[PDB]
Each structure stands twice: as structure tokens, then as C-alpha cells.
Length: 145
Ligand SMILES: *[C@@H]1O[C@H](CO)[C@@H](O)[C@H](O)[C@H]1NC(C)=O
Ligand SMILES: [Sr+2]
Ligand SMILES: [Sr+2]
Ligand SMILES: [Sr+2]
Ligand SMILES: [Sr+2]
Ligand SMILES: [Sr+2]
Ligand SMILES: [Sr+2]
Ligand SMILES: [Sr+2]
Ligand SMILES: [Sr+2]
Image 1 (cartoon, rainbow, N blue to C red):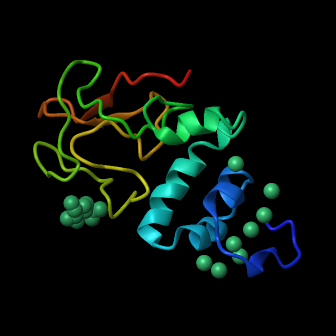
Image 2 (image 1 turned 180 degrees about the vertical axis):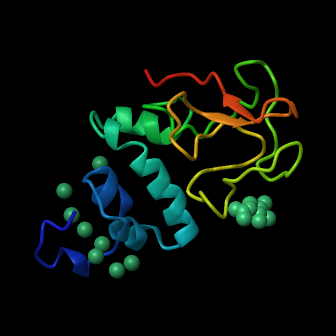
Image 3 (image 1 turned 135 degrees about the vertical axis):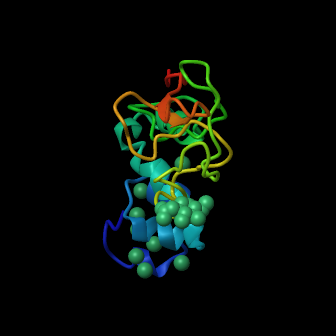
């Protein structure tokens, strides 16, 4: 957190610098090493600033199974929509070409055909659908607590 005074002369540490204190991306970055690791992190972090306290609710929100807020932190496995349709490969370009991928929103675990919300859309974690008919649509992901 930089509570000043030769604290930056010591090894980076995630518990202590970011889980235990609020942190700058540069603090994570120093504590995490790899940057791909720092993109994923930040993304989870930044979607969990609304649930930083208790520090038990933060562990729930970073875990990724439940959705908090509009669930930009959802990192779970639900893959079929609200209508029941099944999601498209974010990787895939058919039947609809995604405009958000990995290149665009990389903190965001766009793995498989999983529900995600790179975008923080108001109606929650969603995905691209199979139906040539319907492009994208909300998913029914569990809510945190
Ligand atoms: C979206 O990501 C794919 C990789 O799967 C890439 O080939 C495509 O060019 C990207 N589209 C945009 C963001 O340019
Ligand atoms: Sr620090
Ligand atoms: Sr500190
Ligand atoms: Sr540091
Ligand atoms: Sr601790
Ligand atoms: Sr401290
Ligand atoms: Sr630095
Ligand atoms: Sr520093
Ligand atoms: Sr370092």
C-alpha cells in the first residue's frame, strides 16, 4: 500500500500488499511477476473493490464461482443462457463474430463458451449464442452470498 519508508526495499507479496491492503497495479505487478498473471489479477481485483470488506467476502468474490455486482468477476463454468440456448466459443467466429475476445478484454477469462461480462453489462454474465437468431444474451449465474 506504500505506507512509505523503505517498505519498497522488500520482496513483493500479494497477501500483504493487495489482499491485506488496497494496491496499485504496480504493486500487484511487483508481487505477481508475469504480466499475463497481473492482467488476470487486476481484472478480478477491480471487479471486487465493491466487496473488499469483510476480507471473507473478498475471498468469495475473487474465487469467481458466485457473481457480485453485475458479475464482472464471475470466473465459473455456466455455459448455457437464460433462454437455455448454449453459448458460442469466444474463440469461434460463427454463427456470430465476437467483438470482445482476449486481445480486447484479456483480464477476462474468455475460456471455452463460458458466461463472462467483459463489459459489465447491466443484466450480468452473458455470452454469445448459438442461435444465428440471437447474438448475445444473459446467463443465470449464482449471486455471491
Ligand atoms: C478477436 O480475437 C481473435 C482471436 O481468437 C482474433 O483473431 C480477432 O482478430 C479478434 N478480433 C478483433 C478484436 O480484432
Ligand atoms: Sr507496497
Ligand atoms: Sr504496505
Ligand atoms: Sr512492492
Ligand atoms: Sr493475512
Ligand atoms: Sr499492513
Ligand atoms: Sr515498479
Ligand atoms: Sr513499488
Ligand atoms: Sr519484484
